[PDB]
Image (cartoon, rainbow over all chains, first blue to last red; front, side):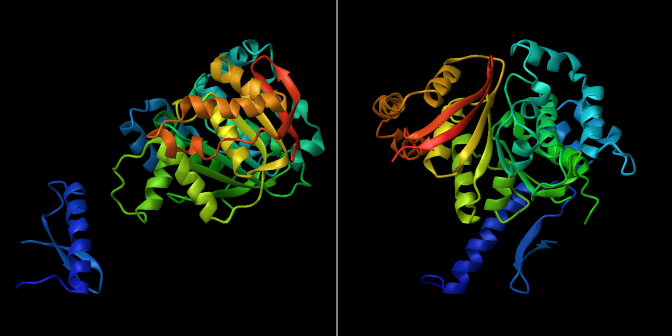
Length: 49
Length: 323
């Protein structure tokens, strides 16, 4: 659980982190609460539910 | 229509939105689309009195046909790279638009013209909001039903001589889209200072080395950054103006900026040289030091000649380069 993140994690957290902020701004009650996910090397916003 | 939605938002009145539905060019008719959208503007927005006053207040200057007037068929139709450094604070948004459209109108009389490239810079909060209304009006004017995009130049055939055109609208929206790789979320601040330099960054990245042959300069809003003298000076600096570039400054309001511009362009080499230096000692501070105005200072050795003048509207041409 300890130590510096690996190359991929550094990328994954930084990129999903930026999208999380975007997902907040890009929100309305009509658009469901997401989980910032990764699929085919593409960041995707899946529903938390 | 997508534009009409963003308009109602940016505090723009119903007038503009409404116009984009009463706007229709007849593809069949002998009268060119640019002239059709040109008349439709004066008809809907009533630019009849404002143009009369824009003429009257400038000593009956033919604001109407400024190029047609000074140039001849060849000279006008030979100009191929135009940069219009903003809209004039003294005129309404439609009159500015109408003027833009009218410039292209004059530049495309003949059918024996090498393609035109017109760039229009909307550099402040007041004008930027109308860029998409301006691009829609141009998409019609040039008749891009030849074969619109969120970002990108409008191509078509324009004027009486069906001249090939490529209209480039440079603005902050386009700048914000570019920086974020066209990401949906563009709601972040950009200052008009930041803006001038990203324009310069794009020109330096785009590999543009085709020279400006007609410079339209006016009384832009946000004088602090969007200054005419400071605008001219930077283009002088960067080797961006053609050896025989024409420079048209147009407005109604006369101010210190106008006197200075006039005294620089119209001034003897010693004068020009001292101005560049006086500004440098007077305005440069260690905080200020990095500004584009401290790097791209002008070239006193560029010589101009008065080619036309009617109180507050003038054409000067680059006469020679001292070295």
